[PDB]
Length: 563
Ligand SMILES: [Ca+2]
Image (tube, rainbow, N blue to C red; front, side, top):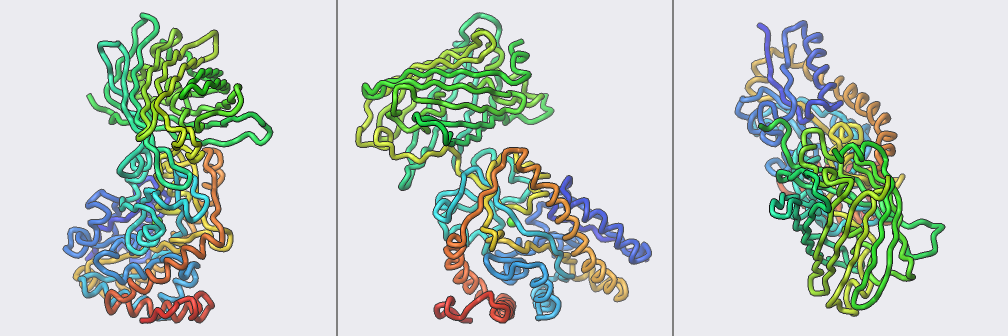
């Protein structure tokens, strides 16, 4: 009669990808005269993304539109049915390998053993890396917390020193906001009723220039200066992205600072001084400091825009050379500029205390070293928001990372994520939570996933129930959609790159030498996955022959590796 197939895709609703997938279901009805209908489902609507394989195998779903290498843990061949690092890197090469060099039937025999019919690949895009750490060379990957899709992709970055996690794309945004895993620099804000203010305790990790890390434990309390009513918040956190730079025309010891601050951590829809921040507000900071008796003064000026959460400031040490590293002063040197979403406005203590302002006190303990004690008044002086600070430091090793100036000029939480290409990652908001894009050099712009293929895979019993004329038409339909989908994604990507620059994202290009370093790690990983079983061996053997044929692999660089 009429055949109806439920098919869930890896694409989340509200991506370019899902819109294209939805149009595919209409094309299939057209091409089959209404006889085959595909009911489309966005990611998660029927089962979790990574649960699609078992759902289709058992028939809960009739089919799926996944990224094929998601099955790498249970079907090694699938790590070879989508690009892997520094291998074949053009869409046309993967088309050739699939449709004339044996790939399609290699995939179909492997999936038939699982009760699945692999229809064909779906072309898509390269992938980008979105990072909160400025990763400018190979060695900067060490200690990064990186989301990736498992398999060989994760193994390559793990071998370069990264910690890897596996998450679906629709969960990447909140993960990047919280450090991806293990630790972050988020400040949980808690009401302090007895001081009619707030308190917070958090831990900053300062990178040591030669490796590894210097911990700075922060204790914080805030109390209003005046007696007007303030807002006492429910639990929530502030997440800050900070960029530190230098002014090339400034000769005093200084720090140029750019920050983006968002309040979060309250779920939407659960059962006066704010007006002063509706536009751009000038800022002045003054700090008078004394660390082990080394005296100094810092002045800063700039502005903040709480509607955006953006701060722009320049700081100068006016007494000469700063005796401590500038990154150790970032937390001391105006949380009233945080961007609070509409549904969280009632939790903004910092703006509620203005204009008379608030006192901010901290103790900051550097592990195995001295401590800072800081006290600050933050308030309006006229129309300028001012932060005046006294800082006193004691018990520091002149030997140490602080007085020895051994800390990297940086301030970030080490989180980064690959997912897909720039347009869909923009659909998911990555530009808001990561201000760097890490790409390869112009010779090798995509190091880990240059050809990130989807597919259609159908429950094998459902497939065999379909009359053969509709089978062939569905195969044709998928092959046509592979390139319609590709073309749609590529068009959106053209629109997305300018939007990244407007959001303040910087594109960082690694070097050819960085690529060579990845390549010496990638080739052994190819052979290890290839040897897992007979399907992965067959697919890599034919890909390796092809790569040798077009000059992508030399025999010398294998250094003895063979199947
Ligand atoms: Ca990816």
